[PDB]
Structures are given as C-alpha cells and as structure tokens.
Length: 39
Length: 48
Image: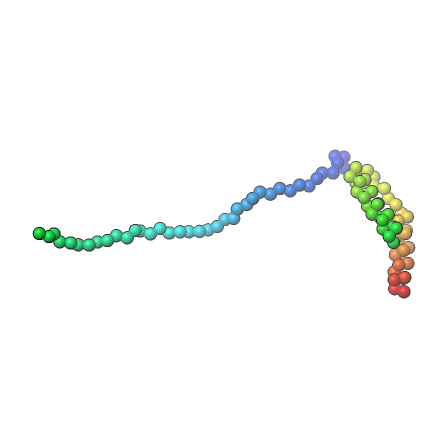
C-alpha cells in the first residue's frame, strides 16, 4: 500500500525418516567334558 | 477479435506494470463495449 508490495519466499530443511529396528546378541556356547588321568 | 485480443494483452501488461509501481490502475470502457457487441455478434454468427 505504502511500502511496496512484499514478495513471498519458501525454504524447508531436510527431514530424515524415523525407523524402528531391533537386533539381538546371544550368549556364546560352552562345552563340558570329563576325562580321566592316565598312567 | 484478434485486434481487441492483442489490445487486451497490452492492457494486461499495462496493469502489471501499474500494479508493480503502485499507481492507480487506468481503466478503459471502449474495450468492454467492443467485447459485448462482438460477443453477441459472434455468438449469432457462429450459430448461423
């Protein structure tokens, strides 16, 4: 009107996506033997 | 038709510049009179 007409603008940022992923470890295995003593 | 059409587009860029500079938009009635008369004329002649 008195200040001349303004000018529209646009800006947007980069929005990464949210993912839900779940993984597992495991208890390592073990061995259990029995032996006798030789002569 | 072509004549008042190019007149109309000239008037359009006129209004563009006038609104850019914020002046009072100049208004013209003879183009409207032309448009109405040739509108009825062209509708009847196209139907014919």
